[PDB]
Amino acid sequence: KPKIVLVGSGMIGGVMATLIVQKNLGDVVMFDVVKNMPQGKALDTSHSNVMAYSNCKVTGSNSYDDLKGADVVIVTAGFRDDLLPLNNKIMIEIGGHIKNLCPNAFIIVVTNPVDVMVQLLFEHSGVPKNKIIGLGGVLDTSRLKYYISQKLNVCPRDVNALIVGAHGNKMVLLKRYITVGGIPLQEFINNKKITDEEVEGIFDRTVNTALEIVNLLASPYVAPAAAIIEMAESYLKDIKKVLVCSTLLEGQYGHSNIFGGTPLVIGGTGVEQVIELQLNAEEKTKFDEAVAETKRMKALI
Amino acid sequence: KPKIVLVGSGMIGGVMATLIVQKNLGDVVMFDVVKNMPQGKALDTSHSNVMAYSNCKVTGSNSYDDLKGADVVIVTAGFRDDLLPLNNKIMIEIGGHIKNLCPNAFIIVVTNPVDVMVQLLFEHSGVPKNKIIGLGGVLDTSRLKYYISQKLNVCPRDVNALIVGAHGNKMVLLKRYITVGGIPLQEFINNKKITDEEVEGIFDRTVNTALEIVNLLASPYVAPAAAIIEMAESYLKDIKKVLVCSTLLEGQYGHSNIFGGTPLVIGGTGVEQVIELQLNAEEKTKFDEAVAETKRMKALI
Amino acid sequence: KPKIVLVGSGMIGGVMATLIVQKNLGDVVMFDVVKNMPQGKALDTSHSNVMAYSNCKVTGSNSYDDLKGADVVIVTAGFRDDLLPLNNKIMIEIGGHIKNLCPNAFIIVVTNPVDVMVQLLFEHSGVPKNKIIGLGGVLDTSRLKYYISQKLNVCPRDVNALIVGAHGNKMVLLKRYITVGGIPLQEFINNKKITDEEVEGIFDRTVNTALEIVNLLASPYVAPAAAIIEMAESYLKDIKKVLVCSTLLEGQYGHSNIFGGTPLVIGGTGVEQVIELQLNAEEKTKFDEAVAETKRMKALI
Amino acid sequence: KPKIVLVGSGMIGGVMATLIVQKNLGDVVMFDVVKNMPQGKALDTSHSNVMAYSNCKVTGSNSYDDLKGADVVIVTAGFRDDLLPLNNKIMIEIGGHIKNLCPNAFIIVVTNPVDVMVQLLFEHSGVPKNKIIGLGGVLDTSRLKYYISQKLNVCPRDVNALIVGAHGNKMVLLKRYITVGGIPLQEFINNKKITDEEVEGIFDRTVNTALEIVNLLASPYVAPAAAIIEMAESYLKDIKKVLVCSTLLEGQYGHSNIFGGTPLVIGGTGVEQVIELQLNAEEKTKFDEAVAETKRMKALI
């Protein structure tokens, strides 16, 4: 049975464990530095195996040895430049344990700013570049896809969209790469089913969604968890989905030695392909600005 | 598209909305008297439609008119005898809205003490007796089934067990009615795969599980949500599952005018059958004690 | 519980009934003019409810009254111009029963040539134009999507493609409308991950797939059944998927009074939108040739 | 990705491949000695990956080397005592290839008479006794469970029942071990929801179901395929379901050196437990008669 370790058992961790049991994906360790809490969540979640017809062990842990033999490790733990050293320390610690205990794990990093933190954990863990990625594009594009789908009254999954560069305020929303049922969004604009102005409003809403939800006396954890589990499941079941995630750039987009958000393929060997978009000059300028902010923060460590 | 209204958008409500989207079961209204919070949770949850390949609207509301045309209403709202009047007031209010806005809804009550509150909402809403039930047995038995399954190393769902009478400390764990893969538990005791003492320990753990989880710096909401959605789904898809829930007793077990936990069948018309267990005298004594506590609290309203 | 009637219980019908039970989608009537056969298939299939955790009645019938109250009707029955009158007779008979017994059903026609037969059944049944469609594009594009996905080593569903006009040898494969993870196929050609020549080979293979399978001592029924059930499920669950199907053209593509393959949206009210592709002149010429063959055969009835 | 090889690509094989793709369970090889046919079925089935959101390779083969690295092997190939030598020859051939090419595979045998043939393949393949079982109980009990569920108007899966000894006319239907929602069937008889006479009629129908379906101008393959895939999935996902299958008896029921139908647990290591029912004397007499027929035929090889 696959073993999935959640390093961080906050709200996102809770939904992830719930979904893993629903999908019968693997045994789950809910790890956290906070005592008792993950044990309680794990106990609650384990009972849902009955309703789900599943058989996944769900355990809680404050003990790093439970990383042993993990097939997937998802890192949400962490404490705005002033947070960079603190969270780097966490990545140092986690990285050591990964190298010691599950060097062959597929690693998904969520800790913000994710495009910096994923590279830090890469550096501190020594795992292969095809075995560690950051959450970004699957989540951000889920917002864009959903809002467009509601304007056009179609199934959310039938909207495809790419958001690249970085996860955060400089995320690059590529209008040219939006399709609906495989059809260019521009055709729907031409047919007056949606306007350019509605699309720009949706772009603004997408960039600011975390803020919107925070201001609504909540915080995002359901969709982040679902995005992470889509990525993890594509690895565990070798589905080879095309998913936009943060990955090491080795020449793509003219960049090296930095992680950035780009479409890639997740299969049973990890990142099987990194897909380099043929961005035009203006799109490329936006991509470069996103990654430049990642570089700026990386240089501060 | 079916419409499911969650009256109460706390932790249990959050997991319920998540699961409804995963299962593509229906549009969801997350209702709460707390402003903004359900709107935030609903917005977050709606994005997960993309990952789930679903198309369920998820909206938040502080407005009771959103009960209009609900097919299923799940009540978790509410504020230990001294809480009975307070929560009764809530049931009065909700009941009026149900009668006005969704008199044909299937109603699942969770507010504790559930066996009292479900009858109060029945009385204040005027819905048919086959259209309103309380959460209890599916949740409690999920604990018992799970713990036994881990002792015997089998799939949790392959353990069947009945817990009856009431949801709470007087719940009746019927040892005679435990089976594993359809086989009496006694055969596994005879074969020394599990002992009577282990089973009694598991009974104690089952009764006190909420307390265990609360003491572990958490609180149960994942398994409660999964239990509720199993009940709701059996109604919405006319599955006719046998599920132990709190229902109006009309002569069964010698009781009338009171709700108690018993196996029943949930299908597209609501409670299609109430199954009366042929309890022996000792089991019956325990059942009567559970329901007597429900009567005691009902008499205080 | 939804009621799905399969008018025709051959191989495609068998797989459809199997999938409906797996998905717990509705009660199934397997209708056929051949005595006993559908009763046997239905009996076999009904047992699989146990393995699937479903509760769908599956019955066999040689009796047209079992169309009564059908929510979905799928027509595969039928006996190459010389077959047109014969199959028209079948559509006359079925049409009468539909009008009498399930005038509100959503109708999916498969009988070939489907773009002619769907219009004949429309004419003989009197159902609204938004409530009857023909199988074509979902099946044909499943071939194109699959073959491209195997060249590029990605999840089959992540390839999107449109095939329009008609189902049969004149089907129009729109190279410009192929995307992979939302990205234009041309980018993958530019990057030498696939060539124009491979794509043309795949186009030829797609057009001739039925012939390939027939020559391999088989015949296609699994993918046709899966395509039909994807369409039916989008209706039954109001998913509003964008699916390419044969539908009445009322001005789109400059055509009237004829059915043709085009992207459309299937939701709970039937065809909720017909999407008119903004074809260029060359693409339009191919579309017109496909539909001209449909017109030619329609004129022979 | 797990690899599942179907040795035999007839009707049962076709449904198995279909279900494996629906469940995204693994790559599939459809093997058959008949040329071209499995290649055609495999090609058809592979396209359904698009509709299922799956990524399973489906290939056809007449070449035994495609057994290499199989995780699961399902044997339906084979040509009434006079058929025993013929089918034994097939088991000799297959057995050699298994030992050579996939000695660690989990093997499910279907070829009739299954309780004899599974032991022959065990003997000719050299695989461990916990890694090879025969289809019987899951299929037979699916009939019994389904028919009882329709009498009582409950979800089919909520009926549990055990049928033991052998698969065929001497199958032992254990009335004492039938439960409904975990409740003894006898309670439903006492309450006049079903009679002893109805139950005996259902027993007769269960024993003779294959004959019923054959006489209805069909033959059973959907439910057999679903039963086999339930067994295979319990292995592949380590679910540890309790499933009644044919397995080597090593003292259980007083028998040795023979395979018989009994509840057992299927998990990731194969047969993890063989559960010996505590049969009473009369039940035991019936069990012995079933297994005696298996012994009689085994002695003829």
Image (tube, coloured by chain):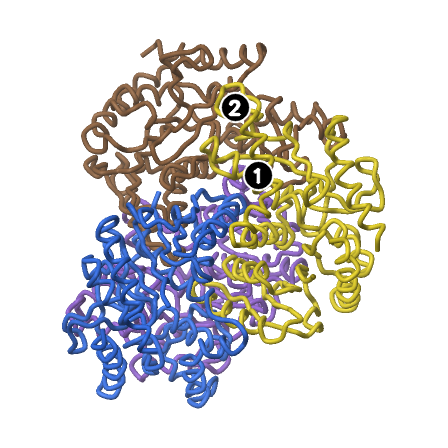
Chain colours: A yellow, B blue, C brown, D purple
Bin the neighbour count of mark 2 within 10 Å (Cα to Cα): few under 14, some 14-19, many 20 and up. some
A252 sits left or right of B16 in the view: right
Q: Split into 4 quadrants, where in the image is the N terminus of chain A?
A: bottom right
Answer whether labels 1 and 2 touch (C-beta < 8 Å).
no
Q: Split into 4 quadrants, where in the image is the C terminus of chain A?
A: bottom right
Label 2 secondary element: helix
Q: Nearer the viewer, residue B295 or B284?
A: B295
Residue C120 location (% of width, % of height): 31, 19
**Quarter holding residue B179:** bottom left
Viewer can see residue D40: no
Viewer can see residue C118: yes
A276 sits left or right of C116 in the view: right
- From the image, tell me which residue sits under label 1: A205
Residue D156 location (% of width, % of height): 32, 60
Residue A266 location (% of width, % of height): 67, 47
Residue at point 44% right, 62% down? B12
Label 1 secondary element: helix
Report the label total. Answer: 2
Chain containing the residue with disc 2: A
Question: Looking at the image, is C28 positioned above or below residue A37?
Answer: above
Are labels 1 and 2 assigned to the same chain?
yes
Labels 1 and 2: the sequence-earlier one: 2
Amino acid marked by disc 2: Phe
- From the image, tell me which residue sits under label 2: A188
